[PDB]
Image 1: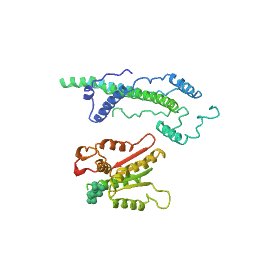
Image 2: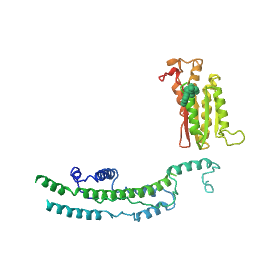
Image 3: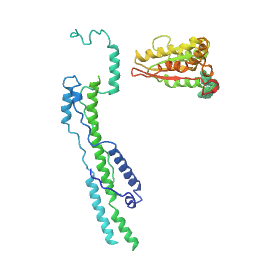
Length: 103
Length: 52
Length: 54
Length: 161
Ligand SMILES: Nc1ncnc2c1ncn2[C@@H]1O[C@H](COP(=O)(O)OP(=O)(O)O)[C@@H](O)[C@H]1O
Ligand SMILES: [Mg+2]
């Protein structure tokens, strides 16, 4: 979770007039996702089985639940979107350096 | 002397216990709470952010 | 000349748009992962707690 | 004459017919012709059925022609009906009480004869505890629900009464 700190007026000076709404929406979603990552911790509290070993008088249901949970493969979502914005950044840097040599 | 009986010679206390258990289950959930939960998962949407 | 140099300064500042997009992708994926872990934890604990409560 | 009965009848029309559970109307110290109107309107609209057991409303009436004891306890009778429906049936109950103020007023009318020193505005000294004993039974428990609509008369338009 290594993020790139961003100036928020420099981000504004570089936005053409056909995607001002898109820049504002990206900004709003950045703030929303920061707030939502702040309002939930990193790792769920793995509850000890103690309160469920010595307080459940049922035949191994707690035990098979804990076995099925210890070996669960929860799907980690893949990026599938950062590579293409990296390609777009490369293309944009190319165009910008060309225009700068013209200038 | 409660081997042959579940609730120590009750002969009653089921007509209300079933309503109580109905309320308790329906306020804890609606699915079957005796089996492991299967997990449907979703993936966040994403748009055409590419520079127009 | 001054105007052209300022245009070059803005071109130098350009990269924040793609920084923003990458930040949002990473943060959305992290939020989704943590919400999924909380969902699985909550369901397991909730069923165990229904058992203990009955 | 500001529209308490009109509003409570509108609520009976808008909620009680569309209601899935049972309903209890306690007329407390009100017009008897209003009770007759409600009875016959509920018969017309099928909410009360005189021929089979599909009726959905129970009526309990002690009206303004009744001595103060009946006017003081008829609200409790309606509460008892609604409480049975809430506890032993587990149903969701609708309880309309028009008018609940009469309850308090009826107590006032007997408070002097019971030999008690009057409180403010001549009311019984036990106004708040009597009202609390009555009203705490009008409630939703975790055994069943009671949605309660009570028309409350305001004497001489004084809300500080
Ligand atoms: N929703 C209403 N629309 C039009 N007139 C109303 C309405 N409510 C009350 N009124 C008028 O006020 C009068 C008194 O109605 P009512 O509800 O019986 O008084 P109370 O407050 O004593 O119960 C009605 O006859 C009617 O003329
Ligand atoms: Mg009225």
